[PDB]
Image: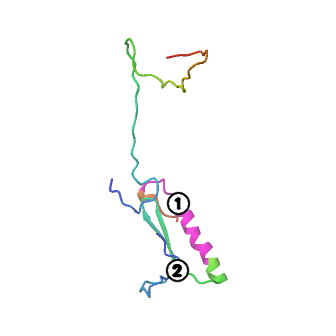
Amino acid sequence: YGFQPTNGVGYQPYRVVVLSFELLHAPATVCGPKKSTNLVKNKCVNFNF
Amino acid sequence: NSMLTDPGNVQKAVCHPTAWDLGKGDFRILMCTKVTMDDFLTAHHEMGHIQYDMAYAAQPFLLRNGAN
């Protein structure tokens, strides 16, 4: 490719990244991000730590 | 990229309406347009060469002319 800056679109360079997820088998790994809040004190509450 | 008037420089540049098809999908019009209905019409004429050029740009290189 002889790329030049004065080239119509469709002739200018594009960078490409191809992500390919390939499963297999395991006991655990990456996953979503859990949410949280601001714990309190001196109040019957329903909590998860 | 196009140069629709003669420049703000006193610039020596052949002032003649024309439509260029440099390649690689790069289309430029070279004219020195004045505010007249004459150059309002040749603007429509010179854009017609561009829209003809943009249409057959998917053929191979040796067939990118008019049909005759």
Of discs 2 and 1, which sits in the foreground? 2
Question: Magenta: predominant secondary structure element?
Answer: helix
Residue shown at the point (38%, 15%) measured from the top left: A24
Q: Position of residue B47 (x, y in %)?
A: 58, 69
The verdict on residue B51 being magenta is: yes
Q: Which residues are magenta?
A: B42-60
Q: Which residue is mark 2?
A: B5
Which of the pair A13/A34 is nearer the observer?
A: A34
Q: Classify 10 Å Cα crowding around label 1: few (below 14), some (14-19), many (20 and above).
A: some
Quick one: which residue is furthest to the right in this view?
B37
- The chain ID associated with circle 1 is B
Is A22 situated left or right of B68 in this image? left
Residue shown at the point (55%, 16%) measured from the top left: A47
Which of the pair B6/B60 is nearer the observer?
A: B6
Tell me, for residue B54, which label it has, or none: 1
Q: Secondary structure at mark 2?
A: loop
Q: Amino acid at mark 1?
A: Met
Q: Position of residue A15 (x, y in %)?
A: 39, 45
| Inter-mark Cα distance, 2 to 1 | 23 Å
Quick one: which residue is furthest to the left in this view?
A2
